[PDB]
Amino acid sequence: AAAESSIQVKNKGSIKLSNVKSVVNSSGKLVITSRNTELKLIDEFGRTKESYKVPYGAVLAKGDGEQVAGGETVANWDPHTMPVITEVSGFVRFTDMIDGQTITRQTDELTGLSSLVVLDSAERTAGGKDLRPALKIVDAQGNDVLIPGTDMPAQYFLPGKAIVQLEDGVQISSGDTLARIPQESGGTKDIT
């Protein structure tokens, strides 16, 4: 089958995410800030019974410390969806996501859909070499939006296989996706 849709932490206990510095988006949920998503389930004696590493951009369910009941979904990611999610509310400004250099413009409706696709490092072409495929996120006013905490604009360089629909001129909430990365892996026979 090879889904691994969600983590059903098999027993009751706390959840302490170590080596991760994420933030709480406006959906009241928890963002995925890096690839160090250490999902550590505990017991009543303080014993790490389960440990996980969730895809950076797999929607988080609960927070930290709250004793989770067993078999519960602790984070969220569709089978072939390891998406790169936004952290705040922001625009879609074409800089290094320039149509024509890195993609094929298939424009859609007022919602701003498409069938454009962004790929990882190796799978790139030779056209947009000065284009590091990205998405420059800016607020409603226009200035480059900021992830809460620092001074660097929110810049999510949406990695491989990720299909992007939001076209120039779409402002989203804090917790919506920029692009969604498939993960089929049907068979799981790839390890010597």
Image (cartoon, helix red, strand yellow):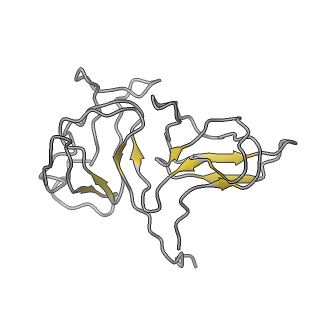
Residue in the picture at 77% in, 44% down? 13
Q: In the picture provided, is 78 more to the left or to the right than 111?
A: right
Foreground: 73 or 25? 73
- Establish if 16 lies above or below 80: above
Q: Quick check: 81 left or right of 38?
A: left
Which picture quadrant has residue 143? Answer: top left
Identify the residue shown where x is 23% and y is 36%.
170
**Residue at 60% across / 39% down in the picture?**
62
The vertical placement of 155 against 125, above or below, is above
Residue projecting furthest to the top: 141
Residue 192 image position (x, y, % from top left): 58, 79
Image coordinates of residue 188 in percent, x first then y, are 54, 75
Quarter occupied by residue 137: top left
Query: In x, y percent, where is residue 134?
Result: 29, 44
For the point 56% across and 48% down, the residue is 75
Q: Nearer the viewer, residue 65 or 99?
A: 65
Picture coordinates of residue 163, whole percent (x, y): 29, 55
Q: Would you identify the image quadrant in which residue 145 lies?
A: top left
